[PDB]
Image (tube, rainbow over all chains, first blue to last red; front, top):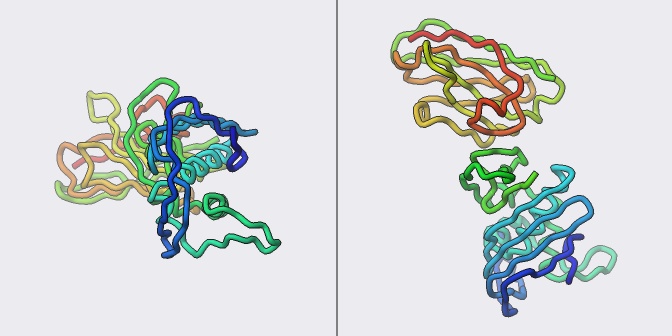
Length: 161
Length: 120
């Protein structure tokens, strides 16, 4: 098990093959990322939030998240979007990403994207995409403005209060 | 927490326009999703539209979509309903509601208003 964004990730089902890919950000900057190519299921465990993740090759399929605060749910969603490696998240980067903090702390590209959206995630949520939802027991929706909804939700995100 | 009172109703000609307003007196207006319902004579409440806590994402009914708009100003604690190309069939009492969820279920809204008469 590995840690990412303060969340503990564990693969429960599926398989993937790591592949290096060169991607282009929204600020026209190149990055070398290790793409886990294949279908996978993960469990995300944090101090204030918990979620179940489903992904494919650079595609988030399903994220069922719970937590104590609306802020703690936002934290889990962002991490899942960055871990998904989707193009909607890469192309939402507004600025060139550094790989070394001011106090010489080297960072890998995936942690570079995580810190960029942990700071400001308005562009990510706006351009991630919304989708209609069906009245399913224990599953509610949430909008790019963290507004709960029983009719729409951020694409693939379903809060389980 | 929140009270709701609607205004702006009255008689208009078919094909007219009427912007309804719903003023709120409460603590955290910004943290409340809103909606508009309407009850025609001899019929139950009908969903018109809902709106996000920010105001960015709105959703309307199949019978008013394209002719009606829902908007809110969180600095004045008011949510408005734009009514366009009004029809004789729009004649009903229009209600204002507030709650936690952006929905079509009248039961999910906790705080309701009084209703304003609109006749076309």
